[PDB]
Length: 212
Length: 212
Ligand SMILES: [Cl-]
Image 1 (cartoon, rainbow over the protein chains, first blue to last red):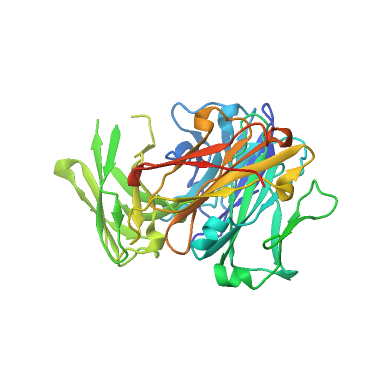
Image 2: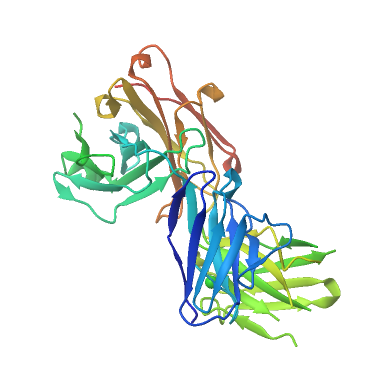
């Protein structure tokens, strides 16, 4: 019953920036609040406990402040090691974690290049059709993909996957895969992926006609 | 202090596992889990030997300790798909360290059997050719368990390559695509081959991706 909410969910920043993450509790937890860092693949690392106490060996650029229902983590000058996800934890009553705040690398806007791939004849012999839409090398991460089949908007028959920020150019790429049975695939002609993103002055659609 | 975890593995729905966390080198001891793509979730604690549980696991998991073995356990019964996660143990001071964390043990709840992936081409055509640049790839579909690896041209092509994180399909098998962007001018000159390896099934596939 003690809900913990962090803000923002994602923060974009540059090396050398001063960064602030907020954590709110649904009822007072006094000073019983901890902050963690977590990197992909690894156990979380404690940074700060009792709201403001720096854990042994943790860099002095991390600091914690606040009490009651509102807490802040401050990183005074961001370093490359600090791009990661951060979690607050209340420990007033058992442990409850906030939802995480991802700190990612800021860069200029870049619109995705969009590509569509029909299913291979080879796969169709399996009885299934996968149609793939690629959004390549874009920033920021927020994007929307809509599938349209003979102009009809689709829902619940697709899955998305996104890369981690590229280590050289700080972009993201995304795949959306529409999956249909062969029989369902053969009912329709026109298959389209419609992409919305900050970098595009209007949505981009890539499409093909089945068999053409 | 070191915490050594074990006991995680693959089990069918409805099955059971016992996790262990052995300490070497007053306490509160916790189990905390992280499902794929999700945040940290506290699940159980032992503080008298007072025990507490999150609502999500109450009635199915049991926390205990053997002081003679310096070992913490988590008995997990009636397992479900949604229990699939990395399980960490953490010790909290009641050294100058406040927390000690284990490295995690992976729990997978699934009735899928080991299965090598299909490998389908994502062929470049006009529908994946924007302003001198073409996209191509391979769809690596319907394998279990993780992971697969993909190379291009046996490691000779690395530039432009994006291999997406796997998605779990509703079938219970994994799927991903690997893509690459190349000069559209290279499409008749240079050959492109994806090399897919799935160690659990001893699968190694080379697929030529031919342009349309
Ligand atoms: Cl939690």
